[PDB]
Image (cartoon, rainbow, N blue to C red; front, side):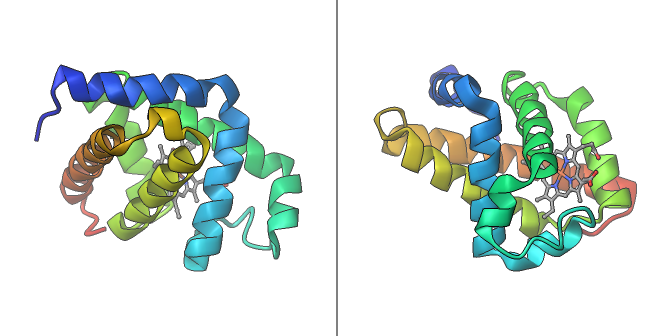
Length: 154
Ligand code: HEM
């Protein structure tokens, strides 16, 4: 699949707003992910002990992790589809070390869309959401392909 320049513009326009507060968006996304799909928390040995949203918001380590995640995703989105190099290390670690199924990548994609919709309604109308969904679907499609090459069914 391929996004048009117009669709990429919608994606990068709202992403520019996210970048005004990377740490805050990361926390919101994780909290949404862990509350909606608790099973995903079990994959994080360093955070699986967190019991409440309050503890999650107070975790300095979780905040730092969120920044790393959004920074990596932002770098990929900014490549506008030409992300082969960026995807390699990410696919290898998540398939071989962390063992993250594609289903969980779908769950975090849902959390990202939920948070953007909540925080940036003016820059996340129907067309913008459609573009972001398309960008995330492309990301998941390419990661899934790499997973297969690496020997992980995902
Ligand atoms: C938006 C998609 C995602 C991106 C861009 C992303 C990115 C990253 C990055 C950059 C790291 C640090 C370096 C590395 O180990 O590769 C990382 C670590 C990790 N990721 Fe992800 N990730 C994503 C989704 C997920 C999901 C959905 C899960 C599981 C529910 C997950 C589980 C982990 C774990 C367990 C670690 C290691 C954390 C630690 O060091 O304690 N990731 N991720």
